[PDB]
Amino acid sequence: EKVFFVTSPIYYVNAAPHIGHVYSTLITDVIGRYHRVKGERVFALTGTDEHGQKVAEAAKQKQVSPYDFTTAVAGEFKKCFEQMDYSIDYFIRTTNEQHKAVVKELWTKLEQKGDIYLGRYEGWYSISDESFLTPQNITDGVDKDGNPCKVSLESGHVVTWVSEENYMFRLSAFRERLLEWYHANPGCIVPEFRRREVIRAVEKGLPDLSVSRARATLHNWAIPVPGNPDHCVYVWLDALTNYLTGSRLRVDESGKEVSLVDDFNELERFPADVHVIGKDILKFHAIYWPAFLLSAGLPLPKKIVAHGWWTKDRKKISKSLGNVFDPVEKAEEFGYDALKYFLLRESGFSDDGDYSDKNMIARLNGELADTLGNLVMRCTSAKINVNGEWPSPAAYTEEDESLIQLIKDLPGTADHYYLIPDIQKAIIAVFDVLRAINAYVTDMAPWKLVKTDPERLRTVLYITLEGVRVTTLLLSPILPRKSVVIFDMLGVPEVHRKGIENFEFGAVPPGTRLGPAVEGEVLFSKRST
Ligand code: MET
């Protein structure tokens, strides 16, 4: 029994925030939310990666001091995530003094167990990705302007040769112990094919890792290696330590950090239950990170879910090349909950998704408006629900027991998808049941039963309300604002809107009064063809 701990990756602050970071954090936010809906202590963590050469030089380009720059951008991030209506507990910055204490404390652990030694790194490097790459992983390409140069195959960004005396981590010694972990825990990297990638890599062989860099190279914009001011710590070790730092910070209601604890157990968050990340940063989390943690004798995480990169109208995203995709703007256009749904629904973690205003409307009209929207407006109209209450149900037909089974079985299958995690599958799961409820309703024809057979209408309405309820509960994390509006319409008491107990069918007693119906309001609004 522990605080469920879920992360988004801390984002480089070299440019403004955009869909990549928003999507990543939404997943994190959703996973966190669901576990809270369960009624569990949760700790969600997003943040910014502010040190290193990439950011140091991005500051230099705009021609302002990095101290000013990083605080400026971090602000654009805090603003945007605040606009997206997330429920992240704390927002972490690698410039934070408590974080340094941790980073240094972690360093010394690695040093005291003798897994750090002074060496050299002579090889390729991407500043834009802050990644060490072998000659096999680089190719010919084009300079930021004219000239021929070498680029990364992974990312297409320029690589420079580096020949520095660095401090070296014995990553090569943790190959065998990594492969046991990949096996021992064969659902610890999601999705499965990304797990096969990681194993295949570690199987080939692992070099040692440069965990320090010549102070000059970095423009002194990093964390000093303990005992040697000539060096600074690899921006990635710095960043990967964010998870441990955040696990150790007591946090006030205003959201400001108020204290760094000595030991990770004191807050019961570490090790992270889930690390949400993107495909592009897999090796750091799936190879380096566990190797570090093993070295330092800390526990390893439970799950790492890597996702893909987005597009718009089948063309990659770029502010400069004619195809932008501003989430705060599209959220203001179509609705914040609606946009989150689309992003979570349209593409699963094994896929590089495709937004378009066409499909956004298709799914908004088809699913949000027509499936779910009509269902809540039906079972709560004056027309069908003449007493504005939860009716007491008569005897159940087999076709009733049929639907009830779905509704009963739904929580458990959604629990699994949410836990994998596979948020797409979980949404579909729910909607299958919503579709099933709209069939049952069309078939029972309650509009007609209000005059023919009120004793029967009681059993239909009840099942429909309880269906809509349980489905809405399990969509809570996806549609946080709209689920509340739904629950209000239904008149579901606040105690019943959360908690594992209210997954069970029949948790709201009959006689429960519905919410006051406002005439002007709809739940979802259709858009043009
Ligand atoms: C601690 S995970 C770091 C992620 C990295 N800063 C990025 O934005 O890709």
Image (tube, helix red, strand yellow):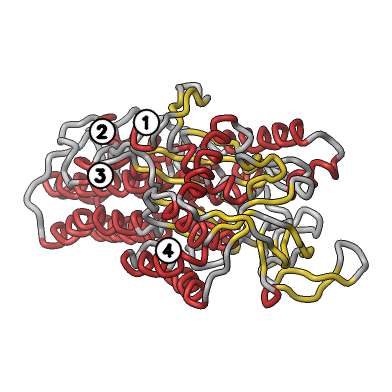
Task: Confirm or deny contact between disc 1 and disc 4 (CB under 8 A).
Answer: no
Which of the two labelled residues, at mark 4 and mark 3, occupies the earlier sequence position? 4
Which of the two labelled residues, at mark 1 and mark 3, occupies the earlier sequence position? 3
Residue name at image x 33 percent, y 64 percent: 185
Which of the two labelled residues, at mark 1 and mark 4, occupies the earlier sequence position? 4
The residue closer to the viewer here, 503 or 437, is 503
Distance from the alpha carbon under mark 4 to that under mark 2: 46 Å
Which is in the foreground here, disc 3 or disc 2?
Answer: 3
Secondary element type, mark 1: loop
Distance from the alpha carbon under mark 1 to that under mark 4: 44 Å
The residue closer to the viewer here, 481 or 146, is 146
Which is in the foreground here, disc 4 or disc 2?
Answer: 4
Query: Which residue position holds label 1?
Result: 517
Q: Residues within 10 Å of mark 2 (few under 14, many from 20)?
A: many
Distance from the alpha carbon under mark 4 to that under mark 3: 35 Å
Which of the two labelled residues, at mark 4 and mark 2, occupies the earlier sequence position? 4
